[PDB]
Amino acid sequence: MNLMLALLTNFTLATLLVIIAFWLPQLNVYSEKTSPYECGFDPMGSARLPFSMKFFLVAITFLLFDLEIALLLPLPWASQTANLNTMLTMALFLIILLAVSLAYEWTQKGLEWTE
Amino acid sequence: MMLYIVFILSVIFVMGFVGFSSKPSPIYGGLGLIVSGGVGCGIVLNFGGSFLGLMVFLIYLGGMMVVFGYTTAMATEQYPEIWLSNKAVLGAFVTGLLMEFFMVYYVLKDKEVEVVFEFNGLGDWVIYDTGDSGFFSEEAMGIAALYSYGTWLVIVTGWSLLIGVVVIMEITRG
Amino acid sequence: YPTKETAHWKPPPWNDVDPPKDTLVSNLTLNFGPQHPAAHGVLRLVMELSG
Amino acid sequence: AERVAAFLKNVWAKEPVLVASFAIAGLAVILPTLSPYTKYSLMINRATPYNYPVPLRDDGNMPDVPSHPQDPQGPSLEWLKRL
Amino acid sequence: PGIVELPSLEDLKVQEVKVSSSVLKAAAHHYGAQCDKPNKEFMLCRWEEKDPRRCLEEGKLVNQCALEFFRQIKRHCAEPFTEYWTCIDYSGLQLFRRCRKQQAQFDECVLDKLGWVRPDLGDLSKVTKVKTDRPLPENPYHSRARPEPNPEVEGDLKPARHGSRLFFWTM
Amino acid sequence: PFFDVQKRLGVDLDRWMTIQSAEQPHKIPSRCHAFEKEWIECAHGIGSIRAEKECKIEFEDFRECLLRQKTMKRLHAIRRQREKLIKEGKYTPPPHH
Amino acid sequence: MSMVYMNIMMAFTVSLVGLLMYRSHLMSSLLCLEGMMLSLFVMAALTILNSHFTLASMMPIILLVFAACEAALGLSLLVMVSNTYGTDYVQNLNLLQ
Amino acid sequence: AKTVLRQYWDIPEGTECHRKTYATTSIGGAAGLVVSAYSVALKTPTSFLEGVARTGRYTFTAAAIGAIFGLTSCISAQVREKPDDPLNYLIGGCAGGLILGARTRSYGIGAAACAYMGLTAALVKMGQLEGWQVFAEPKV
Amino acid sequence: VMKDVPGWKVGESVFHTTRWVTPMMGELYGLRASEEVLSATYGFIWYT
Amino acid sequence: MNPIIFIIILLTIMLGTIIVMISSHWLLVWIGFEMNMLAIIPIMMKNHNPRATEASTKYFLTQSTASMLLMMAVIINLMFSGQWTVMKLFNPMASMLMTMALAMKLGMAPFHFWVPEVTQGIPLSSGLILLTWQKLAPMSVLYQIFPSINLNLILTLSVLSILIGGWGGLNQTQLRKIMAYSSIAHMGWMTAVLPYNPTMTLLNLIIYIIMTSTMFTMFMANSTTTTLSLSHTWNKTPIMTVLILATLLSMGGLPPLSGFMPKWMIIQEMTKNNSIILPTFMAITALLNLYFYMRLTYSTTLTMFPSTNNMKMKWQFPLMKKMTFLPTMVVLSTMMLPLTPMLSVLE
Amino acid sequence: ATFQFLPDEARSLPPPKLTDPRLAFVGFLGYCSGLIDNAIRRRPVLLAGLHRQLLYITSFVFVGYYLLKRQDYMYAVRDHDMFSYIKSHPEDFPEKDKKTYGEVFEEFHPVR
Ligand SMILES: CCCCCCCCCCCCCCCCCC(=O)OC[C@H](COP(=O)(O)OCCN)OC(=O)CCCCCCCCCCCCCCCCC
Ligand SMILES: CCCCCCCCCCCCCCCCCC(=O)OC[C@H](COP(=O)(O)OCCN)OC(=O)CCCCCCCCCCCCCCCCC
Ligand SMILES: CCCCCCCCCCCCCCCCCC(=O)OC[C@H](COP(=O)(O)OCCN)OC(=O)CCCCCCCCCCCCCCCCC
Ligand SMILES: CCCCCCCCCCCCCCCCCC(=O)OC[C@H](COP(=O)(O)OCCN)OC(=O)CCCCCCCCCCCCCCCCC
Ligand SMILES: CCCCCCCCCCCCO[C@@H]1O[C@H](CO)[C@@H](O[C@H]2O[C@H](CO)[C@@H](O)[C@H](O)[C@H]2O)[C@H](O)[C@H]1O
Ligand SMILES: CCCCCCCCCCCCO[C@@H]1O[C@H](CO)[C@@H](O[C@H]2O[C@H](CO)[C@@H](O)[C@H](O)[C@H]2O)[C@H](O)[C@H]1O
Ligand SMILES: CCCCCCCCCCCCO[C@@H]1O[C@H](CO)[C@@H](O[C@H]2O[C@H](CO)[C@@H](O)[C@H](O)[C@H]2O)[C@H](O)[C@H]1O
């Protein structure tokens, strides 16, 4: 309960502040005021147009690396096993294969952003 | 009402799925999936799987972050679609919520519901284990056994992740 | 066996390679200034960006 | 041994970060083999009692099984008291 | 499918050791040594019978030995023992290491008056034998008779009579 | 398996996780440990064709432990009746219930 | 079955219909695939946790690892589809009719 | 289908034709709907009406074939006092083939449909008289 | 509670075996207060 | 692709199949399928053209969906049995989901639409892997769960596959689409006999693989991917046309060729179970496969189509493709009927 | 045995003769493969690479010998199982009381 109470209070306070912020100030709304900002001159095209990702290959590799942590995060518990000979071999095996995958992408220029 | 904590989360779980299954802009589909991951973590947490719950939430938060980046580059249009902006999206969204509501209404109205298969609506607490006094988490011992017992599982998973890096680079090198 | 639904079908390319699209990928155009901390207040630098 | 030294010193000047990594990674793999304390780690993990020590039904011929926890028979943790 | 046999509420009644866990934790080490025999017999019963109903009587002897244990502390070491678990009770994790000074006072009190010795590290986790007159249960799982195995195919292997006998083939 | 290389070579690649009556870390037992073991021991060596018929009791009990469908139906029957009697002013729960 | 299963099973079905009924963006369909794994992960975890089968507590983790590979594989293909046609629309993938 | 198929065989041949025709009409309509679902899914109609208009033709064509088969097969047996006669289904099968040809505007289909549907139905009647299995239970 | 229900048998088992079965939460706290049930089921998981 | 990378990826494709075949645990079987799909896509994309990209995307979407249904079946089996062993499934809904999941992975009708397109979009060597090696893992799982498969469902897929494969091949002029539809038709025979005698499923599978491997290897030798391109083979390598003829007639099941054996053995097994209407229907419908095998033999071996002047330049150069195992496979594809009783080794 | 090409119990069966007609056919198949190999690569069919031709024959016979041995063993196993089962279930395989045609009746169908 306590955790749910704590989360509700946090996001309840934040919402109350936004509500106050929107209904306390005097407003004067017109088209020029609310037009999109771009350094004084009108935007040239839509901000919804595609925005090329140069680090796309690193971004996919993050998905694969970001799952190594789930496999490695149990290590503090695994260190309490009776079978430490098997543990340490398998823990070191995973990290090395992760290191090898990183080296492969590095040596094959996968971490360089496309121009 | 609080005894139905897991059921209430599961209702929001399905609603998140209707959120992205209706397939609006992937910006909002990702939002729906983040919510489902959140209450999905809550569901698993309430069954004693704090580690399992927090991790599916963590993994899916990173995944949708990559998805958001890819959406702005490759799945964006001038007028991204919200659930109200399209008849096909709204029709699917409305249909899924009404199909969700009625299932909830009957199971709560009767404490059981038949939706293709019989489901008991007594609350999910009734199936829980009564006794427990071990001085450890059972999920943690089971998960930690991956390194002692699961030698074969570590090899195949480690290999697949390594191959995954090699494969994605081949696929994307036009 | 020709049919009306397949009247528009051509045999595939000999070497399996279809021509690249003539479509031009559009670069984002941005006003960098004048009202910008790095524009010295009166430079309207119109940049074409890819990413 | 001279060719390797030039390479080794060369990488110490260009990629000291990677030199440090491989060295530490190498130590992580080697020292557990050569350490005289590695054996105690498994013994301490073995000596931690997570579960109840279920008693045995005495049949008459269990000389090494103790009758009381304070009896001399049974595994002793004296090595751990002094570790 | 049967009516579960549950004991009467009188057969379940017993004197309860109504003290807090910090009290039990403070006296656990001495309690383990003093009440080992009734406790070990009761625990042997549960892991053999696999039935709480079949071990009730031994479970009452566990309480009667616990009450007698705590009655001796009250007669001779009430005040030193009372400081010690109070110190344990304060801690959020009821840690021993925060009450070593008071643990001593209680430890030499029970040694001087009662002759009790604290178990060494590892003593209470030993597997110990225990003599009992309760007969060993014979079908603790209430298993039915298992189905008979398939009659073994044995004998001397001889060539197939006229070979494969597949249509026209003569071999 | 299709090719039982595990039995031939004696290695144990994945059989350890197959059943909940197998050796668990620190001997933590599953909730339906006894029911599984009875069904596995009933049907051992006799084949599925025979086991489907000669171990229905063991399997049926094991299925009850897994999904508790008969138990939950019984509770819903008791709970539903109490609602009827409580709502009619006929039965009153004791203090502890 | 327990009532939670009703919504988790429903969640899988919703994403399955979500995957089978395409629109235009290929990215939208790749989300319905991650949706199916999420429900499979949750429903496996409930079964494993509730039944106290300790050794399979690692099973949902392994499930996520091979979901990440599929998503990374799916995103890689979306990159090359986009680089060819300038969108991720699935109606552009009809050369092989 | 299992239950709907059973009820058709449940009632005696040559009697209660209204019920027999209801069964075959139901079998006809279900087959038309299944063809309509695949047809619209794989060959998208231009408009929602033409998708309904395409479902209308196929479902009606299939329901008409079954209704005429059940009617003709029942009435033929009733007239001829021969319930378990394979020939009764031969006449039902041809009439159905004629309906397809009539509904299709092509004497080529109507004739070919008569023969193949006529022989197929008689084999069905032979099949349950003699106990032929199309999906046979593994026994050896 | 089940006196006037005809087909009922009080304390019947759902198991063909006579072996003792650990009761689940619903079996043990089935007819009790919500806060007692709530503490028994989610008390530990919710405790801070 | 670096040669070393191709070998490692190629070994991973085999590794996933082997993991499925030696696994006694449903999770490891699913892992094996994922490992296989991960490693095959880069082989499909090897030449990096829009068509190969389309094929890889269509393949990935199909195989991913099947994996989801397969894993769903496994979890349902776990709920109703509490175990993971690879064997019969304890829930009929789990059996349906697994059977359909495997049907998509095989490309059986009506889950067949991807096979013609993926095959056409990728190189011949990749298509050989797709239509031969990729059949092993799903079939090996079907070989273990068949006691719990719904008979009507499996036979319905078999009948539909034979019909749809037979009719689909009649309209094709591309050799890769002909092999796709031929593959769909042959998969129907394998699963039709599966409920009755799983051994004849293995026999049909092996003989199908030998004959399919031979045909792809001969297409690679002359780098032919269309009916007309293949029609020039007589003017460069006359021997090759004769081997294509014999192999094609064998694929059509004509005695006394090896391809008649699996059809012969399957009819025997089905009749022993008093299944007469189905093997008769199957054998006749397979005549559709023979018809579009005979067209290829007409344009390839039994007639001579026109050539082109530039063909004379190829007379001066020898074949340099590896053609690995081709002499052995073609002999096994044609001259094995006298050794039919050797099928007991598969028992 | 489990996952074994030739279980040890198979050694009680007489091995295939080296002059087995089925083994001679296998050897012939190797000869044909050897000839096809010369043909496709466009060498003199009968003469070229006799070292290669001998390996085609030898390898086919080598593999064929073991396949024929396993084939024979699996048929011996089938008979061993069948006969023991008949022994184990006498009630399902009862001897037929065999009438003679003098005692049995057959309706006669004239061919007029
Ligand atoms: C015993 C039990 C098993 C029973 C099953 C049946 C066994 C037979 C299986 C055959 C297996 C395939 C091997 C066939 C070998 C064919 C050899 C041959 O015909 O000569 C090749 C000849 C080459 O012509 P050339 O240019 O002079 O030489 C170039 C090569 N160095 O090529 C040509 O020039 C011919 C070009 C014209 C094409 C003529 C086509 C009609 C004649 C074909 C005869 C072969 C038919 C095979 C089909 C199966 C028959 C059962
Ligand atoms: C295939 C030869 C016929 C060629 C014409 C093609 C006919 C169509 C083939 C379709 C399949 C029908 C096969 C019919 C033959 C198989 C039936 C049979 O004969 O089985 C028994 C055979 C041993 O024959 P057996 O009666 O025991 O006499 C031994 C004498 N030494 O055991 C066997 O199974 C052996 C069968 C292989 C063929 C006979 C081998 C003879 C030994 C020399 C090796 C062959 C070399 C010559 C190759 C001839 C190729 C045409
Ligand atoms: C007992 C044998 C019975 C045979 C039964 C046949 C059953 C069908 C078997 C199908 C497989 C057929 C073999 C595969 C095709 C290979 C043949 C070919 O591709 O074309 C024919 C070829 C001639 O073409 P060419 O370029 O001139 O080669 C030079 C040879 N001088 O090559 C040829 O010249 C013809 C090859 C076939 C003739 C085989 C001869 C048997 C071996 C005789 C031993 C050598 C005798 C040498 C004699 C000279 C010394 C005195
Ligand atoms: C079902 C009942 C019927 C049973 C059928 C049995 C089928 C399985 C039997 C194996 C079939 C393949 C037989 C291949 C024979 C030809 C091999 C040969 O002569 O190679 C010659 C030469 C390489 O020879 P070399 O590598 O030095 O031999 C040592 C191998 N470690 O280099 C060359 O020029 C050879 C090129 C032609 C060969 C095609 C390419 C394949 C390469 C194979 C490599 C060598 C294989 C060694 C075979 C040993 C088999 C025991
Ligand atoms: C590309 C693939 C790369 C794979 C790389 C894998 C690297 C693995 C290196 C070996 C790691 C473990 O190495 C091994 O650890 C155990 C300790 O746990 C040591 O074992 C030692 O301690 C254990 C307990 O701790 C005692 O039971 C044992 O008596 C003692 O020998 C071994 O002496 C050491 O050899
Ligand atoms: C077990 C964990 C610890 C082990 C370390 C694991 C990670 C190893 C990372 C790869 C190291 C070798 O692979 C790496 O390849 C690239 C080739 O593009 C080399 O060279 C490149 O690197 C640097 C920085 O990018 C550039 O300035 C240089 O111009 C470029 O040539 C790197 O000098 C080398 O470090
Ligand atoms: C393609 C969409 C996939 C969507 C998947 C949706 C979830 C599927 C849930 C599968 C489990 C349903 O389970 C189905 O219903 C109940 C479950 O107790 C069973 O109910 C029936 O079978 C058991 C058999 O002993 C008995 O209780 C009795 O015969 C009957 O009640 C069904 O035999 C079972 O097949």
Image (cartoon, coloured by chain):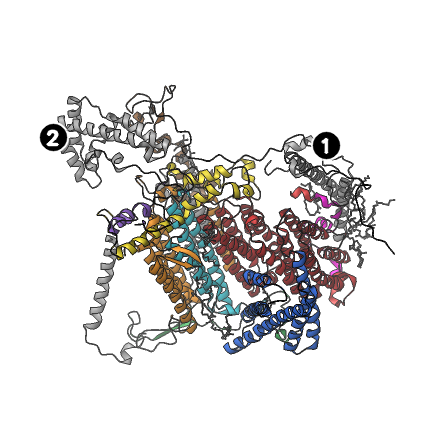
Q: Position of residue E154 (x, y in %)?
A: 63, 31
Q: In this view, does G34 lie to the left or right of J179?
A: left
Q: Name the residue under label 2.
A: E79
Residue at image coords 77%, 45%: E168
The residue stretch that appears in magenta = J314-342
> Chain J hue?
red
Quarter of the image containing the C terminus of chain E? top right
Q: The orange chain is which one?
A: B
> Chain C hue?
green
Query: J142 and F89: which one is in front?
Result: F89
Q: Quadrant of residue F84?
A: bottom left
> Chain D hue?
brown
Q: The yellow chain is which one?
A: F
Q: The blue chain is which one?
A: H
The reply to whether residue K72 is visible in this rendering is: yes
Which kind of residue does numbered mark 1 sit on?
Answer: Pro
Query: C28 and G7: which one is in front?
Result: G7
The verdict on label 1 being within 8 Å of ligand 2 is: no
Q: Quadrant of residue A21?
A: bottom left
Q: Mark 1 points at which residue?
A: K14
Quarter of the image containing the N terminus of chain E? top left
Q: Which chain is purple?
A: I
Q: Residue B167 carries which label?
A: none
The reply to whether residue A52 is visible in this rendering is: no
Q: Does the magenta stretch include residue J328?
A: yes
Look at the magenta stretch and give its main secondary structure: helix
To the question of a shared chain for discs 2 and 1, the answer is: no
> Chain G hue?
cyan
Which kind of residue does numbered mark 2 sit on?
Answer: Glu
Q: Residue furthest left?
A: E79
Q: How far apart are marks 2 and 1 (CA)?
A: 92 Å
> What subunit carries mark 1?
K
